[PDB]
Length: 182
Ligand SMILES: [Zn+2]
Image 1 (tube, rainbow, N blue to C red):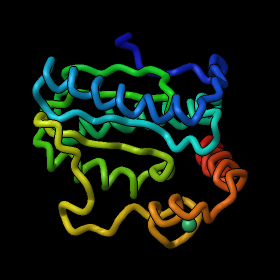
Image 2 (image 1 turned 60 degrees about the vertical axis):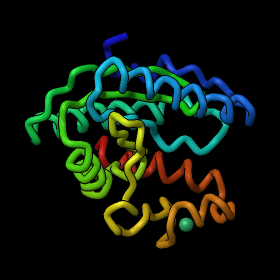
Image 3 (image 1 turned 180 degrees about the vertical axis):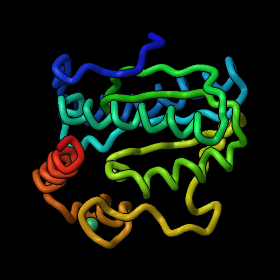
Image 4 (image 1 turned 120 degrees about the horizontal axis):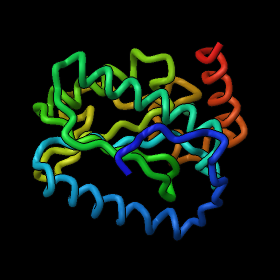
């Protein structure tokens, strides 16, 4: 379970139902709290944008794997010890967790900076939890909210009102993926 890179051709193409997606958000939270108790340091909880009902695809793995490398190089850059790291596939698709012995805020700012500066940064959902279980946000620091993959507006406004077509979100993912993996 320690190992972290998810081989893309072994993707499950598991079609997740709506109530299976709604159930897994509760297992996530519970799993997140077990890591915080086993290692009381901030935790990065990392999933990939996976718009459809099939969220464990070859595309989503290649994207998850690029994030793994970048999370580790960020840890090394900031001089932050990873105490535990694991990956899995859940109802939200590829998922990773890293217990990092760092200040929670620095960690959240670093991962914000990563989502912006990295060529694939907008396919990553890099959450950061404090040991108390508080999920840190851009709003805690009066930062602009995460913007939508497809236009200028905030992600939440475009996801609430299904503004953008699912094929467009997917085609963008392939497109960003192909501009990097050149
Ligand atoms: Zn939009």
